[PDB]
Length: 335
Ligand SMILES: [Mg+2]
Image 1 (spheres, rainbow, N blue to C red):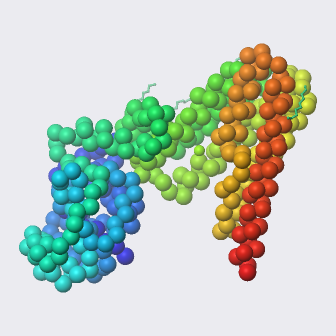
Image 2 (cartoon, rainbow, N blue to C red; image 1 turned 90 degrees about the vertical axis):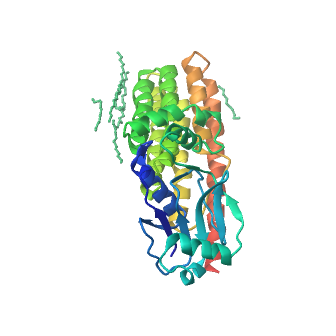
Image 3 (spheres, helix red, strand yellow; image 1 turned 90 degrees about the horizontal axis):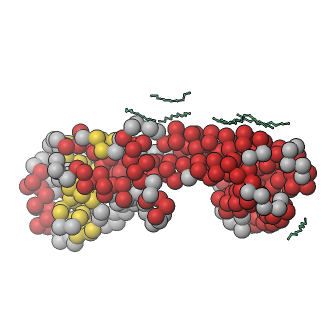
């Protein structure tokens, strides 16, 4: 069990991007596996790791990995100390005194982390920094949605609301516009609300909701979305689209799509893993949407037929890949 003592301060009560700074440092340290104690005066408990934070600080680093004793610094600032179990034999009940004694006893180097010291003046800056920490190599497409995430975070909008709203948007394009025969506009509707995923991802990262529920809902609503897309196609071409062979191929892809998702979900239930295959959910989505949009613009429908065939075949080999690897894992685990 790991313990982290952070000293109480006046600025921790301020709210930044939907949480308090107090809540932000607490949740950050919890994700690093520390149980957090806020203290006006330190009372030490028996434990393994001891993390002492004094100055008010916003930690911008995503994964904080603490291995071995060291001093935590960011750009010249000393944000906090990491002491081992030995500090239990030093600390006599006075804070500053016990720290300098332990510093005289042990020579520890300084490890660099991404963090900013809180001041009343630089709050705007911190906010700017925190938003940029959310991108994490995802690229320009992630960055352009940062003002929307900022807006939604300030308004008290939950990431689940964004996810649900995004899914209702996809369903509206797929189950309304497609059966009407509007393939182009249905597709731009689907396309617009598909990026809501990048928004909830930013928010889930910003608002600290990474939990099993969040993951569950994202997986589930993604399934609802993809199924709706094929459903609309199937319906439209069996009726007003007047193309049964395209409708049959679309229906086959729907089923094949479900089977590709269910293999992986079911494997994980068994403790195994099945993240493999040529066909990936977003990639499958993209080619279908592009073709359907094109057909909605007057392109010959055989373009969609070809794409559905290729997608059927790609789904089949993907299923084979997943089923094969879970078999290797299962048979190896029993022996
Ligand atoms: Mg998703």
